[PDB]
Amino acid sequence: AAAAGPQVFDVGPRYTNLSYIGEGAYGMVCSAYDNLNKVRVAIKKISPFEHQTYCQSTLREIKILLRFRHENIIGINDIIRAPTIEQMKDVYIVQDLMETDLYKLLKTQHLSNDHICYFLYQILRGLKYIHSANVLHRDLKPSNLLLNTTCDLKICDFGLARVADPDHDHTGFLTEYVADRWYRAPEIMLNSKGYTKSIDIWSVGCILAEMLSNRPIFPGKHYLDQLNHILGILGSPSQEDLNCIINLKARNYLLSLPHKNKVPWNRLFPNADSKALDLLDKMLTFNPHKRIEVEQALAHPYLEQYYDPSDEPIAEAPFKFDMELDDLPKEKLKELIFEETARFQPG
């Protein structure tokens, strides 16, 4: 067994010359030389079978990523696992090596207006496809946008992804949420479980603002501070937008807040392309009903150099039904991961 930071990292014969490249969610990530494609690849070791929760996320991410085929979504090249359920303790997911991500890039690098435009285009092109598959990403943020040396962008990390369920999206005030606070739409704190496509557009809006300045636009320190950051820039919601929040604890909370006026995008982003700010305004709209749709954002003037709807494909095979993974035991989820990974096996 090849070892890395002496743990097992046992990746076939086909993957040699291993380099540790950090610790992801369900285990260790390395780069490795692929002997059959003569390219270096990324390999993620996953060890989830002890915990029903880890099995859930692992299965959901593998099902989604194996069904999707899109230039702007990370693909699975290979899956290495034992030939039997009994011997399967770990799963290794092989993907294209991406030298960096937008989080790492924004920490040190100024983006040109052309880079911001091209990166935003790729994000929306990939999100069009996800949404067309009736899937919500629910955790879009810079660190989940992988980049290579020629600025190709790939969305990753479908750990929080769900089948869209706009009809069952309503919930109480202060409902607990897992996804990164700074990219959460205002409605997640108010009355939304985040089962509508408009939650992803909000996160993309936050990412565009972060690309314009190299700083998060809404870095809230706690759940309610996230709302104060949002309303500090957008201003107090209008009567119309409030009238759409029927939940009394959420409405009366917003009514308790001192009045705030909007901060103009051009004051926050004096260097920014006016078209980028128009589109940003439309993405960071408080009312999710009035928020711009992914396809409208691709059609916005800011993206007119790239916009080509014939080359912005939609999914052949949407997830029409909810993935009822929450009440399956560990053991069934391990069998389903085994079945889902079976196409990569010799034979």
Image (cartoon, grey):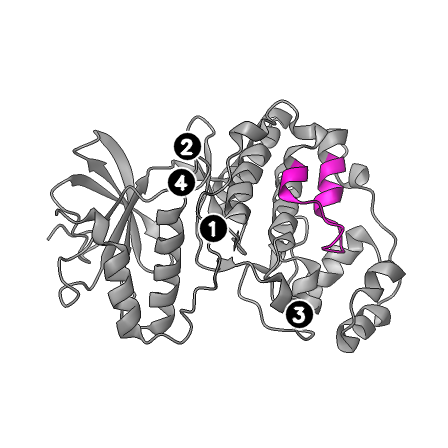
Q: CA distance from mark 3 to mark 1?
A: 23 Å
In the image, 328: left or right of 189?
Answer: left
Going 55% across and 39% down the picture, which residue do you hit? 123
Label 3 environment density (alpha carbons within 10 Å; few <14, some 14–19, many ≥20): some
Q: CA distance from mark 2 to mark 4?
A: 18 Å
User: Above or below — where is 3 with respect to 13?
Assistant: below
The amino acid beneath tag 1 is Pro
Whether residue 318 appears in magenta in the rendering, the answer is: no
User: Mark 3, mark 1: which one is toward the viewer?
Assistant: 1
**Mark 1 in CB contact with mark 2 (< 8 angstroms):** no
Q: Residue 328 at what x, y percent from top left?
A: 36, 74
The amino acid beneath tag 4 is Arg
> Which of pointers 2 and 4 lies earlier in the amino acid sequence?
4
> Which of pointers 3 and 2 lies earlier in the amino acid sequence?
2
Whether residue 279 appears in magenta in the rendering, the answer is: yes
Q: Which residue is mark 3?
A: 170
Q: Which residue is mark 2?
A: 148
Numbered tag placed on residue 318 in the rendering: 1
The secondary structure type at the circle numbered 1 is loop
Span of residues in magenta: 277-297
The amino acid beneath tag 2 is Asn
In the image, 328: left or right of 218?
Answer: left
Q: Which residue is mark 4?
A: 69
The secondary structure type at the circle numbered 3 is loop
In the image, 209: left or right of 43?
Answer: right
Label 4 environment density (alpha carbons within 10 Å; few <14, some 14–19, many ≥20): some
Q: Would you identify the image quadrant in which residue 154 lies? A: top left
**Mark 3 in CB contact with mark 1 (< 8 angstroms):** no
Going 83% across and 42% down the picture, which residue do you hit? 264
User: Mark 1, mark 2: which one is toward the viewer?
Assistant: 1
Numbered tag placed on residue 87 in the rendering: none
The amino acid beneath tag 3 is His
